[PDB]
Image (cartoon, coloured by chain):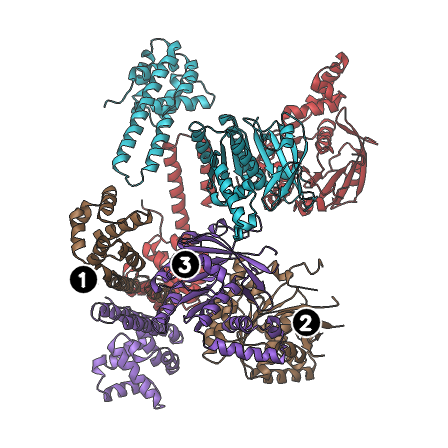
Chain colours: A cyan, B purple, C brown, D red
Amino acid sequence: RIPPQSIEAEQAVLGAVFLDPAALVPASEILIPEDFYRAAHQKIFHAMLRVADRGEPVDLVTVTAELAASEQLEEIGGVSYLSELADAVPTAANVEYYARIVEEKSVLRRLIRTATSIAQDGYTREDEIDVLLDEADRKIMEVSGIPTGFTELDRMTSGFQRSDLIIVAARPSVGKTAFALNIAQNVATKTNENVAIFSLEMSAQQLVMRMLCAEGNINAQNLRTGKLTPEDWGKLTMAMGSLSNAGIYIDDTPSIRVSDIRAKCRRLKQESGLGMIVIDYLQLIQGSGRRQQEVSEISRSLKALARELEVPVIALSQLSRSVEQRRPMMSDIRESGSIEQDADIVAFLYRDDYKNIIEIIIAKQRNGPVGTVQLAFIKEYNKFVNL
Amino acid sequence: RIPPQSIEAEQAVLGAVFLDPAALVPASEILIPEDFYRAAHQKIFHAMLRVADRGEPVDLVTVTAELAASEQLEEIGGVSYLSELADAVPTAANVEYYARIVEEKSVLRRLIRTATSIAQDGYTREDEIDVLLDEADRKIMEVSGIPTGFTELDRMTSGFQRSDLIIVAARPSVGKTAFALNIAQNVATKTNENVAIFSLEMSAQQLVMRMLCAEGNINAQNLRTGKLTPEDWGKLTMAMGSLSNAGIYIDDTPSIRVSDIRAKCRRLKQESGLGMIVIDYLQLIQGSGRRQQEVSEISRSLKALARELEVPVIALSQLSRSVEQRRPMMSDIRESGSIEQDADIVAFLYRDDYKNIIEIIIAKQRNGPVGTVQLAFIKEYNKFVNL
Amino acid sequence: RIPPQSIEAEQAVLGAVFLDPAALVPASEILIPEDFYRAAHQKIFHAMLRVADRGEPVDLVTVTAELAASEQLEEIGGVSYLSELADAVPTAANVEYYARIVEEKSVLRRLIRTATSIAQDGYTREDEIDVLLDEADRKIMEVSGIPTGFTELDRMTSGFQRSDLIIVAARPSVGKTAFALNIAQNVATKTNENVAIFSLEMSAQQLVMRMLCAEGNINAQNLRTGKLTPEDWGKLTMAMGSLSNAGIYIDDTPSIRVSDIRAKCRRLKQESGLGMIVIDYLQLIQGSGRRQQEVSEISRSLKALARELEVPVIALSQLSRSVEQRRPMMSDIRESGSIEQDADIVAFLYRDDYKNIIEIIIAKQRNGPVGTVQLAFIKEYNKFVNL
Amino acid sequence: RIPPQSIEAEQAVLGAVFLDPAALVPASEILIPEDFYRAAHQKIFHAMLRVADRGEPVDLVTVTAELAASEQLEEIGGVSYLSELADAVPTAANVEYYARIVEEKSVLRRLIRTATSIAQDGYTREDEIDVLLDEADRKIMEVSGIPTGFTELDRMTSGFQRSDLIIVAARPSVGKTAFALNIAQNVATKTNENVAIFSLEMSAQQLVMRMLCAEGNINAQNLRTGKLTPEDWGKLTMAMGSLSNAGIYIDDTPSIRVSDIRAKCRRLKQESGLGMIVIDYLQLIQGSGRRQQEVSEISRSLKALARELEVPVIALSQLSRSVEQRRPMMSDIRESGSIEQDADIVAFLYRDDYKNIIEIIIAKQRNGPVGTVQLAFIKEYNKFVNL
């Protein structure tokens, strides 16, 4: 003690209102009744606000009436006290400055209260800690382009650029995961940039297995059922050697929230440098809770993630079973929107023959053309090659 | 105290008989003399019954005579008391209701007596217990590694080892039941070990039919629709002969709890010796009550079962419809966990072509590699063979 | 007093863990913290379990740390007490036996507690009783073929056999109720077996009216509007005479649960003998609560009912309006499953002409053929006759 | 004090039941246990009712038993008190009169209690008032044709008559609002009757703008974009002059409940006189809560409103998008019923050419023909004219 306060300034604020009713507007903007340290002043300010909300004139008579009806007049010192308040104001026009003093001392009391609260929790719960530090963080604050490797896709895009949200949608079995991994692999191994991969459905080793096969040309099923030709084995050592130098960071957390994604990428860019973010399908990202509105916020958040880290974000998406009812188009993700607006580039993967060829339909691109880029897919190595 | 009683109702029952002799029939049906709390009423009711059994009229005079001869008149209060009883009945026709009240309070006294008796025995004999609980039950009611046979699977596992919890998950129609039965059959017929099989969905004979077909190479549908080639019949006798020597113990109880499974296996190992436990799908095992938390406890309990009996436990599991949304992975049983941690080995069965070949994906193994072992399935015999 | 306990054994269990950390596994399997009579031992065992769940080594230091952070060290006697525990164990390897002693004395305390609780409720609530006895039952436990009469249907089935769940599905107005009643009537009047009929939609007398008409050939509408030919009346007396000798037990309870059905049939078989169970449509049986998952459990329960009482259970079912969209098939009850698996025999009733003939489609039969048996229906008597 | 009571009459009621069990029927009809001032009499009457609900005979013995089991015998004075009650009744046949005396004194106590409660709230909450008076109203009570102007529509209807609920349904853009306003305008300006208009979607001035244009022939868009020919302006002054004499009362409350509509019309008729009620679409009226059942009650209430004020009620309704799937019919509002029964006259507006002509389909009329009346619509003035 004693708690930071300014009775003189509190008195001047309330007084000002009684001298000029217009003074309540500036005061109410800066203060709420609870900012007043003295209980009587809280009750008085609250009476003023009530009268004001009714569109009734706020003066000594209506405030007196208001407090009389709420049985608070005597408790606050009567009309006689309201007179003193009116005598306690040097100039009504200075009400904002008086108000700021009251506010300043309210904020200080909140700082002291939350700080003490944190200190006490330190002795009590002991008994967690990780949560303690996070809520201590939380409570204190409250008191206040890139080449893709696919020459033909690079022509249209130029290629994937910083701050852009790129969405690659495809029906199951089309090969969207393989597509995203090829791009992530080409960027990390060919260029000097780091790629952050979030695989929510597929594990980290299960994903590396696919880019090892893709890298050194090893038959996928050959590893799965292993099997392995002695020289197909020597093919693996060269794949590892070249793939070890790449800046590939994988997070295989089953169902992350966007905040976790954001925080991890945040730390990575300022620690090692970041160039791309690839997320293995969006419909698996869980919201801030514990699903149409939920998915729009995630979409909106991924675009914000792209802008912040000045990096292209490639988010895979899955198409509704409408294509089969019809070649995919915008309406197939629009029934599952509103990813359509947030994405400055939307790409679909269509397989003409479900020719081991696959079509990459660029349906949306904010700065550049719209059309179909074509690539060949090799099932045995899980790769997309040029044409 | 005081013991549940109704003197008023007792008095009305006896009174009723003195007003209308026909009232004794309903009373005697519902009550015996001992149900009366007051000794005098027991003696009186007993006198009535005696007179009645002699085929003599039951009224105030004959009951008085009866009690006089048994030297009980004064003891029950004389004829003067018998008069009071006659004045204590509101309506003789309501005798059944009066009787039921007396009975109700007799049953309560028996409940209190037996419950107290059980409580006392708890402190005294201590000094048995198993008998105590059984008679407590009784008294309360009265008031009212191991080679698998599949060379390629044995390479990776080595094979199924003691104390391990092995989980074999597969979508319906893939052939998990057939797979588990083949292993159970190979172990019992080839090695000198005993296998305990729990089939909750399939009956004991229905399961033997499948391993008879598997054993001697008999067409499954041939038996189902029977049908049977004379020499396909001689094929059955050899199957039985060889299958009779095997130590196969089957329990086809519809939906057991884990405690029942545990107790049965417990007795078996120390009586004949136990080597494997196979349970036909986990989602059918019911909890300790009367379903996510429930399933975790069962999982946790099966692992404890494996450790206790130093035996591999093979628990079949069913996959969520997520695979079809995608080849199965850990997340497919994780939405139905938490079997993932308790199991030191998790295996999936994937059929490439739903090639009559089937893939056995070992997704988890605590001591050993992770990969895909491949086997061929024969629909006609319901068998898995090597490759 | 004093409550059954073993401080010595409690001390040895905790001590064992401090001597060999492996001792906690056997102890935790047998005991939970609450089994310990002494509060300090509960707190200590709970600290051990917490440390263990974190995958951290459980020894004197980590347990001391755990209790210090939960502010329980002094309360349990300090590290000095933890030392005594370590000195209180004769041999760490005997931990299971020490554990069982602790458990045994915990179970006894629960027996004493629940028994006392029952005794007290006996004096208090008095004021119910039927509920009292049932929960007293409940609480104490917790401390621990047939010829059908239709020659052509008998050919295929052979006929309805013990332990089989037979499901007879039909659209409204087809005549499934009449069909089930004819079978129930043929069995009871022709063979020496007892039939249990559950009619949830139709009353007991309303159902007897239909089998009286069927029995002695009395025009149904004739009774309904009565009406009655003097000799059609003498036809009724012969129907009653012959129908009185039959072992037909009817329960016309509006909407029973499966447990009530089971309990009644249970008592019946061991009291008079039971041969068949007929239930007038499944969709009316209410669940254990207060509807797809609910219906699967009922189905599963009826099959368990069949196995238990070694009796064929005939459960009528109603078809979805899909047939009219198309002759019924399995998919018509599959949208209302999962009765399809539990039933070892599924029969549909199809009327070619909605010929007063009706078709009985046996879509499923586990042991025997699949086909259509044909019978003639007589509207006037509500009967199915041969062909 | 002392609170209005009659112990003598209370005693006679209970006594009567003990003398003649039939006396409970009249007593229970007039009284509930709480009407008895004396606690013992409440307990006794409650015991009687319980015994009675069980279908058991209510006499001195069963009531004694009932109170003994609920541990209330001694508390009410024993069986000895029950005897006194039996002696306290002059004649059991007079039980209704005794009962009414008890009831009378119960009602008085409720009057005193609620009145006191109101008086106290007057000093406390002071601090609202409008709510106070309304609940004071509420609590005290608890203690206890027209020519349309369209000659062809007048032929069929004759025209809109008192007590009739008229429903005018139309798809958006057809012109139902304009239609209703024309009728309301014709009635008020031509005949000496008052029209009450409820516009929930459209404001009062926005609605007057449309009937000013309609009145004096002023181009609608001309006012909207104003614009205005000097003599088209003089056209406005004549429109106002003639429209000022009309008895048009408008309530443009966004989403009223039917009770508010009813109360306002109620006051209007007895204050100035009322002739018509027009409500701008029914689907906007909110229920008594905070939507199919909800809409039926509103419909039912509007018909009651028509009967009460002996006035035709014209409620606009909107059609489902079924017409476009097909000329509107009854089924288009039947999927949004049950307005179909309550309305004694249902009219649809169909526009042949969405000819600036519009069809008025009278689909229902309780007293009169069914057919199509045809009128011409002028978009520029928002008017319907004859033909």
Q: Which numbered disc, 1 or 3, marks the residue closer to the eye?
A: 3
Looking at the rendered image, the quarter that the N terminus of chain B falls into is: bottom left
Counting from the top left corner in percent of width and height, residue C347 is at 63, 69
What residue is pinned by disc 3? B165
What residue is pinned by disc 2? C371
In the displayed structure, B127 sits above or below D9; it is below
Which element type, helix, strand or loop, lies under badge 1? loop
Q: Which numbered disc, 2 or 3, marks the residue closer to the eye?
A: 3
Q: Pinpoint the chain carrying mark 2.
A: C
Which element type, helix, strand or loop, lies under badge 2? strand
What residue is pinned by disc 1? C2
Is circle 2 on the same chain as circle 3? no
Q: Is residue A356 left or right of residue D2?
A: right
Mark 3 residue type: Leu
Q: Is residue C54 left or right of residue B292?
A: left
Say which residue appears at 23% left-offset and 83% top-offset. B73
Looking at the rendered image, the quarter that the C terminus of chain B falls into is: bottom right
Q: Where, by quadrant of the figure, is residue D343 drawn?
A: top right
Mark 1 residue type: Ile
